[PDB]
Image 1 (cartoon, rainbow, N blue to C red):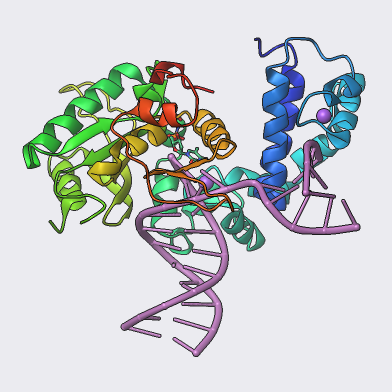
Image 2: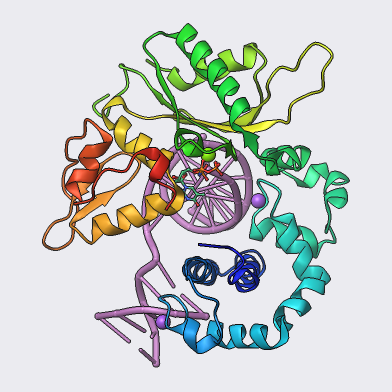
Length: 327
DNA sequence: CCGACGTCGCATCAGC
DNA sequence: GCTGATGCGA
DNA sequence: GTCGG
Ligand SMILES: Cc1cn([C@H]2C[C@H](O)[C@@H](COP(=O)(O)NP(=O)(O)OP(=O)(O)O)O2)c(=O)[nH]c1=O
Ligand SMILES: [Mg+2]
Ligand code: NA
Ligand code: NA
């Protein structure tokens, strides 16, 4: 209901989560802290003790103790300590560069590379993805206003149709959900000559065209069905430049399109809650298909899908439009 | 006591 | 050269 | 770290 009811606590758990993933390299702890952060931020009361919070599904003893220390002292001792730790905080920060995960960050800090400057002084030791992530460190953390998302959509749909009028391109993500701003642009791509049953360079032709009109500027990774890169809007004649933005383009078989749209429309936390319920109801869902689970709990053949609501029907959930799919 | 905790595509690395 | 494992991001 | 077999 409101971030400031227990925001001091949720910040704490979120901070603790990051250090688990990035420094301890313990992903399941990281999730446990965020799972607890989620359920507490939805708690419509100001928490007065660890024991009270422990009633919430996801909060156990160890987190309850920490809330007590926080409520009493207004801080965490393990957190004040790890914040000032040069090794730990450097590793944690370095992972904010796209391409640098917990492993690489630990490897960089170990040979003394602790900052963005140290990184820029050492371009040789970075791979392609990491260099680009370093180059656009600031831009990749900026949000994209909906107005710009719309202009970027204009260029995408236009140039996609120019390569082949039978391409189907849909911008998904938070944009499709109607958010006033997005973190990146998610593009789903579809062509009549590409299905599960079965032209060579369908994804490439779209990418290179977007490169030619000088929209796509860099490539993080590119395979046959999935592209990851950087793009930028053209600025007014003498006006200043737009930030470089992240854009993913994904070629999905046309007969699996709606499972793709649903999956990449999100939201991430919604898309998770859905498939979790689906599994509890006898189905399994991924980016391509929805398959019924057997009596020994094994998946069968992919069911037919001709709309997003079909997948909703299968798992006994009433339809939610993209704008209502945040959680 | 201790195992589960989501999954996909691509770059890169370990190893034959 | 090749297959398979691991790191990574969404 | 938490839940649950
Ligand atoms: C972050 C994330 C995303 N995904 C998938 C499912 C999401 O529905 C889909 C969208 O990803 P996104 O771009 O991180 N989510 P968004 O576009 O809704 O929010 P934003 O404005 O781009 O940050 O990517 C995962 O499967 N695991 C993840 O950890
Ligand atoms: Mg997105
Ligand atoms: Na509990
Ligand atoms: Na990163």
